[PDB]
Image (cartoon, coloured by chain):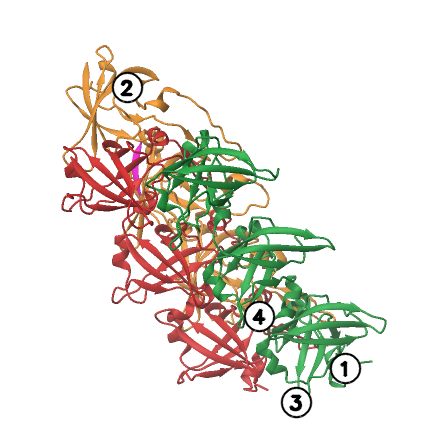
Chain colours: A orange, B red, C green
Amino acid sequence: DLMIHLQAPDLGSLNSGSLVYFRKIPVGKVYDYAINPNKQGVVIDVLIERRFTDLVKKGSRFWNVSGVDANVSISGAKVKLESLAALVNGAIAFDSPEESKPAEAEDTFGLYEDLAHSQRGVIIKLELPSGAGLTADSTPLMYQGLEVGQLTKLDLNPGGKVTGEMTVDPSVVTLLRENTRIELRNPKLSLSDANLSALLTGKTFELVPGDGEPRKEFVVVPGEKALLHEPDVLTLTLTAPESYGIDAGQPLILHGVQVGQVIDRKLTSKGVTFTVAIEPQHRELVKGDSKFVVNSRVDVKVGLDGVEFLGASASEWINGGIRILPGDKGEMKASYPLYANLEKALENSLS
Amino acid sequence: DLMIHLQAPDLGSLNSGSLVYFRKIPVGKVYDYAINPNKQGVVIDVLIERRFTDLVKKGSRFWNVSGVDANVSISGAKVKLESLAALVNGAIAFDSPEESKPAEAEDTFGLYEDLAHSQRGVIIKLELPSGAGLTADSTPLMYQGLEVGQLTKLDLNPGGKVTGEMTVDPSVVTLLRENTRIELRNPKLSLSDANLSALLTGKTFELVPGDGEPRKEFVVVPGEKALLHEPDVLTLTLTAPESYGIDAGQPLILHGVQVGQVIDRKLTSKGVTFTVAIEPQHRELVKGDSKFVVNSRVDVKVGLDGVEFLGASASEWINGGIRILPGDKGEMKASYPLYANLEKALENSLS
Amino acid sequence: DLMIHLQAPDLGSLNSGSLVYFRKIPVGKVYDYAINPNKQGVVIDVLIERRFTDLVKKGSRFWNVSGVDANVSISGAKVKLESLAALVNGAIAFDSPEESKPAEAEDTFGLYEDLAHSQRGVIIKLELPSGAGLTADSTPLMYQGLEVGQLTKLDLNPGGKVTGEMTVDPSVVTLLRENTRIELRNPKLSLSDANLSALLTGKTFELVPGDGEPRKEFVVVPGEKALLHEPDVLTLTLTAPESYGIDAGQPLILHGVQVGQVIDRKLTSKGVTFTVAIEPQHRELVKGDSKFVVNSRVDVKVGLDGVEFLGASASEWINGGIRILPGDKGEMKASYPLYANLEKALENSLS
């Protein structure tokens, strides 16, 4: 027989004589339990049967299957009663890996509290902005619309620094590399596709891959700020004497299509300084010379022969933002001015 | 063996012979129970086993784990059946701290009714405005989006004075100091981020830290009023002959960006007197001389050569509030006038 | 031993041999039960133990704890299974007050059906308008946002007169006095604070205190009418030849701020007579002379040099109501006219 030790933070629903499973086959039983010298944890020593000993490995993980847990899920709640024997007495299930040395001679093991906590994978440290919609064991990592990871830990370090960590699977671990971003998605209001599922899930970690050296720790930034930290991005600080009603997250439009986004708005004594960003595809297309025109205000001129509507359209007005007048050749200077309307941008009159 | 006394307000689901746990290990049993001379409470005396005696400390807390409690939670309701033995007979669990003297010789203990009531921490007294959305054991203290505290008590003192108290954890207790504000957040309607969780939680205590001497009692004010009690803030009483449709909580705008907020509106016999406030960052930027223009009313002038739209924009009109015309140098006088539109503010004609 | 009688409207889940609790300690048992000579009620006589006899008092209340009751509550439903012994056989719990004579010699007692029905307090009779959203045991009395009372009875007397009664706690009983109003609140639609709790609760009795002799019966009026019955209030009957689109509950505005409310609109053969009311603070401020101008209609005049927008603003138009032009000195006469717009009020031309 095999006499191995398990280290648990508490005994749980396990009694002496409760049963140990492999593939839901009883292959042993719990022999004894005792508090170790430190008050922190309970050591539970179990006894595998003589013929089953080979099953346990050095790289085995043991988990606890005891009691009935009921889950309420969106789009229907499937409550299934799998194992009746675990209710009365409790149980411990375990996995056997492919290639590992067989365990022997009172080898210790951590006892995970669930099958989901005993999933293999790689710990990935995150430096989160806030834990506003994040949950300790309930926030997933999406990639291509599929659940790849799970936020497994969320702490508030002193100094006001929210940090967490995440278990990601191996196939994605190969994907993880330098300049690979993890940004949090808000459950944004969708008008074209009416889905309750996105609203119910809440915050959602999105993975966008990159190339370079493999890294195992990332920094998460807010969705508005997320654009700034792209591998390729163009960051322009543009000045203006007034905000002109341009908020921090307005879209930024060239030739009718959104090519960039305003990132943030800072008020100074000289005026309002914006910091806008630009995507890689259109980085070539700006070409270092441009004019910047406000689309947040409407302008109507009435006349007997001259009738004109300037600087906005109703869809553009509700969207708002900054319009680009692209030029032919330039040096991509640091500061640009923000013109009040189009004709003052053609006149080059910022006053 | 150890023979200690527990003081409970009622017996609960505990019978004689019910079981006492440490880390869910049975380490004793309930020996007897009797009403003490005052009718108020029940004294339950228990018996720890001889070898387990060392586990009990002077700083131990005992709590009650008996019966089945089912919780319905937003985004899914996880009902887990942990302990079967507590249903039939009842149980008492207890904690052992790190450094305390061992208890002996019929030492009394308070019996908490739950694990959540037996959490360690520091009582923080609050002087609340009202208990409109507050709950006795269900209102949390957020800090950086994480649950830090729990409103544990809510009373209505005579004179119409709602006061409560709160258990906060030690790491935050270090943070708590003079000029550290606790303000209540309303579940405000969010258009950009659609989250059901904020609406379901309701009122929410937000912690914003400050520096100075550590204090252990605070005064909570309503969210609109909360701005006024900041460590650094500028409070201007500005007069006007009419409200001009400016409500008590309108935003207050310099150069297009909100720099302050109107706090409250008082009607007098001379007119309408507002009291507006100003954030620390823009306190330097006002510089003691300014003009104050209403943004709540639209003004259209039609003409053959003169066409103009004055004092408002559609987003500004729905937002409303007061616009600042900043000056160069002044003394930051007490009273300011509120001009009806911009050209009367340039003409300095308040009539 | 003590042999006392209980009078219940029916036996309930109580059997002979069911158990009697004090602080959930078994201190007796049910001895027998028999129908009394009138068919109305069942007399249940119980037997307290010899040493426990002192516990029962003249001012004791006995209540019934039998069966399992499950409650579904908003923001989560906490179903807790407290007492297992009451399910099979039934139970009776009781309270012992602080200062009362001990009961003896077959003293009768009413048996309340629940712990909530056995709460101490003072019966307060209410003369309700209707029971449209009221519930027999589920409508609370709020004071400062806290639950103070509970509507315990709701009857329809002949003649179409809905009357109910309410148990209020002692501390508030000290507050209850002459000119202290109890008005019912509707779950009004709130745009600034999104709370599901207010909508789910429904109708809600609000307590506003006053001074004078203590009274124990009140008259509840509808929320619109409630203003009229204030301790200090100004009631003006103002005439008009047309309603001008002014509904029964429009706000009434001086200097941009709401100082009063229209109470009701009555159509006569001469015209439309309104009855508006005025709050105590602004009662001094009207000063007996004023003009009354409709804010419910817009007026646009177009001209080459004269452009003007008269009698309304978009927020005022959606709000509607009556505007005051305050005067210097008057006698506070009974009837006032309602002018169609502002310039006819300055011309004093009601035709």
The picture places residue B33, in percent across and down from the top left corner, at: 28, 39
The picture places residue A158, in percent across and down from the top left corner, at: 26, 53
At numbered mark 1, what does the secondary structure look like: helix, strand or loop? helix
**Residue ID for mark 4:** C179
Most frequent secondary structure within the magenta stretch: strand
For the residue carrying disc 3, how many other residues have a C-alpha within 10 Å: few (<14), some (14-19), or many (20+)? few
Chain containing the residue with disc 3: C
- Choose the circle earlier in sequence order: 3 or 4: 4
Q: What's under tag 4, amino acid-wise?
A: Asn
Same-chain status of marks 1 and 3: yes
At numbered mark 4, what does the secondary structure look like: helix, strand or loop? loop
At numbered mark 3, what does the secondary structure look like: helix, strand or loop? loop
Q: What's under tag 3, amino acid-wise?
A: Lys
**Residue ID for mark 1:** C344
For the residue carrying disc 2, how many other residues have a C-alpha within 10 Å: few (<14), some (14-19), or many (20+)? few
**Residue ID for mark 3:** C329
> Residue C208's image quarter?
bottom right
The picture places residue B126, in percent across and down from the top left corner, at: 36, 61
What is the magenta range? A120-125
Locate residue A68 relative to residue C248 in the image: left or right: left
Specify whether residue A121 is painted magenta.
Answer: yes
